[PDB]
Image: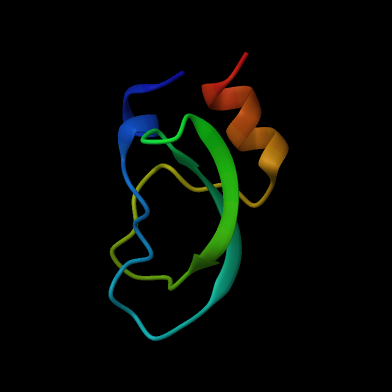
Length: 57
């Protein structure tokens, strides 16, 4: 767990799609999604395992 893990499903307001993983703190798990590129947050991982290893464990 890390402070930024609380940040929500922040796709960010750009018109791109880059498959990433974030932690839905409002559920309590790491989930796949598409990031845009712009205006995201720290709650963003290329792998489930890095998300998991950051927030879970």
